[PDB]
Image (cartoon, rainbow, N blue to C red):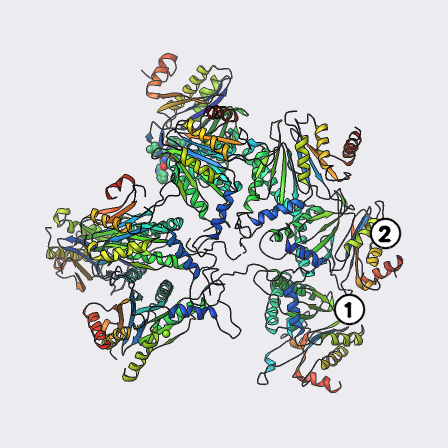
Amino acid sequence: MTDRYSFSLTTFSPSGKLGQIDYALTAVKQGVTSLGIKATNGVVIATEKKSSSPLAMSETLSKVSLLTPDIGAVYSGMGPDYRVLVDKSRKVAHTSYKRIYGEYPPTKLLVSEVAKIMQEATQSGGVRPFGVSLLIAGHDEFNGFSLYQVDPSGSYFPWKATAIGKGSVAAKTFLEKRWNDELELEDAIHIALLTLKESVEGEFNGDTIELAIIGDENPDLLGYTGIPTDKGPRFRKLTSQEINDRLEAL
Amino acid sequence: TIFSPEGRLYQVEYALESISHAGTAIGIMASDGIVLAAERKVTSTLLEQDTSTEKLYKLNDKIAVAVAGLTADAEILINTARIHAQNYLKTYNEDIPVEILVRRLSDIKQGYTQHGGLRPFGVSFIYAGYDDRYGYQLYTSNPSGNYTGWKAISVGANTSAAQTLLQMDYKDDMKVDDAIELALKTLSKTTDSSALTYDRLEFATIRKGANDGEVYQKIFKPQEIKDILVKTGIT
Amino acid sequence: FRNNYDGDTVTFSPTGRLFQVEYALEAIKQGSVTVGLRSNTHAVLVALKRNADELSSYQKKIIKCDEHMGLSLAGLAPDARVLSNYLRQQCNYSSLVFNRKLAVERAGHLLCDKAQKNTQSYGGRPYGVGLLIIGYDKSGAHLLEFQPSGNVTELYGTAIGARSQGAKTYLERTLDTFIKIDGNPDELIKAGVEAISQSLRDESLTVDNLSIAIVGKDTPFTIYDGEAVAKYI
Amino acid sequence: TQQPIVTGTSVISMKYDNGVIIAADNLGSYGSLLRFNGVERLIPVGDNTVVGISGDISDMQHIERLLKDLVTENAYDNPLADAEEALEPSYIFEYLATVMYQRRSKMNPLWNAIIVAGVQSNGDQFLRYVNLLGVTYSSPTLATGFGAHMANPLLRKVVDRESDIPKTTVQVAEEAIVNAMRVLYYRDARSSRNFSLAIIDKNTGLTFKKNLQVENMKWDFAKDIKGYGTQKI
Amino acid sequence: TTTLAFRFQGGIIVAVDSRATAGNWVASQTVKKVIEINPFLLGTMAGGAADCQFWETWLGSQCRLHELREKERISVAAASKILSNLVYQYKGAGLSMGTMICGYTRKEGPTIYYVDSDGTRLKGDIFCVGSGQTFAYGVLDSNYKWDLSVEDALYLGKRSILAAAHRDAYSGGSVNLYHVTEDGWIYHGNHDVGELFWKVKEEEGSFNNVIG
Amino acid sequence: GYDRALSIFSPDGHIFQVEYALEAVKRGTCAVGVKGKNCVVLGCERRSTLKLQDTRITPSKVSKIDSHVVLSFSGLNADSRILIEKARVEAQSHRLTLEDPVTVEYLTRYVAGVQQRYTQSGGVRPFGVSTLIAGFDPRDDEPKLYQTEPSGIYSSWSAQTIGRNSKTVREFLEKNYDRKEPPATVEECVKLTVRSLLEVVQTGAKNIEITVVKPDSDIVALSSEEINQYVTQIEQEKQEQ
Amino acid sequence: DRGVSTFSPEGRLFQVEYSLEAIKLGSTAIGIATKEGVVLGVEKRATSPLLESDSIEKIVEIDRHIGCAMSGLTADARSMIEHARTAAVTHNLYYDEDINVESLTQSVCDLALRFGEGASGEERLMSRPFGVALLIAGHDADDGYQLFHAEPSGTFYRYNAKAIGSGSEGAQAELLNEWHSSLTLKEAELLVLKILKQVMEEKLDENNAQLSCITKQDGFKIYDNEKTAELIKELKEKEAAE
Amino acid sequence: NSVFSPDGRNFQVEYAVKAVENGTTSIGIKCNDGVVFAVEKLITSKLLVPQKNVKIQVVDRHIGCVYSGLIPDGRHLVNRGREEAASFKKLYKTPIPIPAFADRLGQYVQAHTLYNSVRPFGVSTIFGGVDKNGAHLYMLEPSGSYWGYKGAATGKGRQSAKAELEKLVDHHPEGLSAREAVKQAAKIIYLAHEDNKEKDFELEISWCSLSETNGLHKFVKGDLLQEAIDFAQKEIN
Ligand SMILES: Cc1ccccc1CNC(=O)[C@H](Cc1ccncc1)NC(=O)[C@H](CC(=O)NCC(C)(C)C)NC(=O)C(=O)c1c[nH]c2ccccc12
Ligand SMILES: [Mg+2]
């Protein structure tokens, strides 16, 4: 019953810092590495499944999420914050876009809405900022493939390739060295695997690594036939087996 | 919101202090156009220059803003400014005069200063616009909700340094092309980087529309910036 | 212990105490003395009114709540106005809806509950007034003492305010005599007026000083001030 | 806006020397269908009051729930709930009359005609009527629906004014009620042979009689009636 | 009901009848249809009695409030507009009123405003209002001149109400007369139609439809 | 949402936030008003710090509230816009309901009331603004000049000044303003107003702005050239002895 | 700083006590009740000689039979006056009569209570107590001429005579000695003017002090400057002959 | 209130318990077909009217509540219990089962330990009665914690009360009649008064029993009360 903190919990300090946003960014730093690489014909987003218990079934906890048939997200930072942001991102894609124009939002606009939701946790009364950074990759007819980072402050930036979390500095270095504008999706997936092995402590296989792509349309995932102009999602989560296949010729 | 014993607003002053660490944005007004130029905050090789707009935004067909501060705060305000321009267009069947839009935005910022216990927006704007009453105009607004009109101005880092340079070289009879040169030279002199390369800039003009009698906002593609940087002899 | 714990009504001290409520209790002890007592047929309030100045009016301590009920006050006077207005309404509501005179006991319960909410809400203070309530209902005469903690007790007699401990000891001794004073209003007022005297360092209680109220079997609640109290001084 | 669905016909009542009598049949009609046959339309409240209700049965069941809540609520924090602070007929009545009038004023009536019968704590008879409009009245005899047209005239031949009430015994009053119930069964198409009757006496208390029947009916003369004018056989 | 007010050389004449009706029932013959708002302001009443009584009494309160707030008497224009705006809030709810606000101020001179429950507000020199309005108009308009003496103007007022009192079933009782000056209303008495009619017939030679 | 009290009483009986609001006015640019026999002149200083401004479009210090009343201020510029907007709404509302423009006293009492309200409301802070309200009542040739402050106190002045160094210019006007002999005309009334600012400005170029209000809604701002000629004549005429 | 309606360990409301301190810094106001009327007088106290003193409104009409004088944070007094006037005019509307002086005072004191937020039990549309005290004077048929002191504590007292503001400690003792039941209105006027002259920091004249009274016959009136001046030759000549 | 300490405690609730421990002692005893409630009423002064400051409260018709600590807090809780019981009866027609009622109070007390703008209740409450399937007795702490009990005690004399309660559970394992339980409650209240012997006390007993009160809550008064007092007076010496 009723809130006593109807004031901003994020305020400016004498030096100009927004304390709570910095502290949230530190929470992202402690988080498991995730990364994204943009190709000519796709985007790859990848991350490690740091399991809490070997008694836990790690397939019941996805770090890589579909947001629209052509947009997926990954994060580094606080898992539960990510989980609720995914729900709101899914919802806002419908309420602010699909229920208006009868189609899914382009990547930049959806990222824009998520950014807005995060900005509000930075200005509103009685809340702390979200403790996560998201990488959001997608496709849309008029913009093609794209990749965005969203930070706890609500800031977003487009990337050719980036990494967030623990070893992000070493991984960005590793990516700047390897990225070019002629990469096919398979090349990007390969680079994503190499980059991620540096980060991973333990086993490095299709059960401990989580990987998804925004590629071409998967008509076999649509669920129905008969409408030619409907071709299926571009978001595709790679299977454990599909990952192990690419680790043999790694 | 509260006053200090000095008669100052703490949170506003601290917001202003935040802005002085953001990339410099420069606005220059000439008789036949306006220039907006801004320095992108320390970037990386892998940033997508092509699909990036962090400092320059279109408000309507005749008005644009350069941003210094938190981008997410600025998008909040930009969005309401866009709505405000459309409400005016719907009400009067005329494009909104620049000052009216600027005053509104400034009033929103002022509100956060005076009631509600929320933090102010950490944003300073340079507005560049044209209308049939005052022709070309340049305004500035900061977190306090104050706004002033200028012939040339800067916000963000090194405003003091950039302001002195503009004061020296500015002349009332300038054409846009001379103003393009002035803004780039000033950013070059005041950068905290080695060189002022294309990948670290956003650039835009509001001109008399190539050849027409109408008004055109040109937001420079990265390649265009590279050219206009050679022309002015900074390469 | 008293340190960071008396900031609001919404915080317990490490001893389990509510200091804001205890501080509210201290405004009662600061207030001018008032006495209440009863027999089987009548109930009486006696109060010492207090002036600000020799040029001023003595301020009233006695408020009527219904034809069969009223109260005296010690502490923050404007708080007494708030609480008696509520009590006036509760009395009124009872007459209109049920055609029933409010039991003095229920009036006690209602005041307790109202005080209580103010001992648990953030940003609100507790009431800072003590009250003595008298009435004649369907089960005779009654006297109640109200404390802003919300504790209300039924008594044959009592006193609140500064130096009230004297009057209390007197009534404690007088018990078996005044409980029987039936069918003689003037004798009971006299026993009340004598009780309030044990609480005087002040002076000799003048025609302006003294405030008396009575209610009973065939007497609506009535207030006496000025020349009408002379015959008791 | 509403309309009665399942309904229960007359409630009839009168004062005698030492108390009140009230009766109502046991039928719940559904328009012209005599649908339900074990319906109690007399409601004892405590043991000094019977509420008799006619009109809409769903609204009647609502008023039952209210009366039971009233008894519960009166018992709360009340050590005299079965003595001096028990619910009186007049309290029960005023309450319902308040409810009825508020509901009609909100354009959402309880579609009923109600008679409250009982004895006050001072021994006085209480007999009062309230209906869906909030109209209230008292009389030595009260009846609702058809009862007002047919029972009152017979009952008034016994108690025509206030001074006829010392003069009227329990036996005469009950006799008159029972006869009037017979007349109602003869002429009211929505009435029933089975009824309940309650006596509230200042000495006896409450006597509640269930499963009473109309007896001594005259039907033999029917056999001589042939045709509708000229027919002889 | 018949009420009138007119401006002339020497100020304002205000005259009203005093009959209250409910259907064809004569409820009263001695009713007050002028409200004395302040010593310089008058209000007249036609239509719903409660509506008029209540809202013009309310108007007096608002006018008084103005005096305390502005340290000056309210203008006729402003007083009428308060009632006009109130009545407009209630439009379509079924308020029923026909009203004249008549007074003097230095800035305005003598002023008449007509205000009704439709929300109409008009400044004018001559108004007749109520079921008897047309009858009063017939006499008033045919004998009106700007330069009428005070004595004549009071008589014309009185005579116009008598006319309407005679012809309109819903008017009658008595005439109440007022003169408003620079200094500023003066009451000019109650005149019972029972006596006034016969007096006027005799002295004037009019009312020849009437036998005896 | 948020209605926590910020303006409260001190142990010695001041409202700290109101007092600190006064400090904000103290650092605001200077403003002055003096009234002639048949006019009221409004003068304001503009700061030297930034001289690359566009004067065509920058909000000026003297604002029209209605066609016969002006307002100037010292303190937080942004705060002043809120008062000016509300005063303007009230002015139109007054014409709409009373069928007459506001008196200068009425308008002042309204602005002062708004200022007062923000000193006793939860969640809000007082206005860091003091105002000078000047003009002519409808159909009246007698000039009016009022001053309001953050507390909501208001009063009328023959001449007054507010803002930084106002203490000096007040001292000046106290010596130089005579109540029986006011300035007789517009020309000489402006001159006194410029003289009072010249005590504080120290070159006043386009650094001084003037507005003259005459009866019957005749309000005119002065250009640099008209002001220049006043400054020129003041230091020239006052030199020899 | 913790809370706005917090009790002290003594059992006093912090903010109420402090508001009483603000009243002490105010201009002096004095009222004297007689059987021929009540006189209210105030020190105007101009902050500068350029202030037009007749624009200083420290004595206000509430209704024909009620006036009042203020001392303290005088801007706070506007909404108190507005409420008072509305209560009086409203009462007359509901009841076709004059509101009793005492009843009007109680109303003003009810308004003063409503600081805080909306305390659990009802609602408070105000963040701090008023920082102004009122002397409320008038006449009614039941109690005749009356003088009340309205405090931001919500309490009020009737007085035969009362001073509020900066000079109030000195003025009250002076009033203790000078007041008697018999004073005429002319004697009361003169005493207010005398006591103001003593406590004022300039020399008292018709521009830095203001007089008013309330009589049954003429109601509440603020004396113009000519009338007060002619009471100040009078007080000078009276004290000079003593 | 909403503040967890570094070791997962709530100091505010722990402080609320100290207010309870400071209170008068009160008890409940579960018998073979019902429940008995008893409480110590301190006689502060002779002026207190005997039998007239009733502490034990009824809820609906079949539930009694007794409590120790801040009396007003207990009343606040009982008002809520009554609203809560009426609302159950309104929708479900049957009177509220005791376990159902326990949780209602439970959830409400627990809510007051979630928010910085509220304090926990300063009482422990002993309550119960008869429902569809027997007698139940409950005790409820400031934290909102509650369990079923065979016997319960709270307040100043809680320790000795618990010890006498434990002895009964041992010497009577075979289900303690309603009439015995009343007698014993009087005894136990007498034996917790040893701590506060400086001031005199008054005894209040109430009961809800299937065979003795028809499952309704009644106050023990008259001859039954005196008989229980005499038993306690005899067994104390
Ligand atoms: C303007 C004025 C001011 C003061 C005095 C007189 C006048 C002249 N006006 C009238 O006489 C009007 C004529 C009229 C009738 C219907 N429509 C519009 C106009 N009469 C009314 O308003 C009457 C007045 C009345 O009967 N008053 C009683 C009283 C004061 C004379 C004793 N009320 C009624 O008829 C009346 O209230 C009702 C009559 N039947 C009703 C059923 C439900 C509710 C109300 C009524
Ligand atoms: Mg325990």
Is the residue marked by circle 2 packed among few (<14), some (14-19), or many (20+) residues within 10 Å?
some
Which chain does the residue under circle 2 lie in?
A: B
Left-right relation of A21 to C193: right
* Residue B177 numbered tag: 2
Nearer the viewer's eye, disc 1 or disc 2? 1
* Residue G80 numbered tag: none
Q: Can you give x and y, in whole percent of width and height, for residue B94 in the image?
A: 70, 45
Whether residue G125 appears in this view of the structure is: no
Q: Amino acid at mark 1?
A: Ser
Is the residue marked by circle 1 packed among few (<14), some (14-19), or many (20+) residues within 10 Å?
few
**Secondary element at tag 2:** helix
Q: Please tell me if label 1 and label 2 are on a single chain.
A: yes
Which quarter of the picture shows residue C111? Answer: bottom left
Q: Between C229 and D191, which is closer to the camera in this rendering?
A: C229
**Secondary element at tag 1:** loop
Which chain does the residue under circle 1 lie in?
A: B
Q: Which residue is mark 1?
A: B44
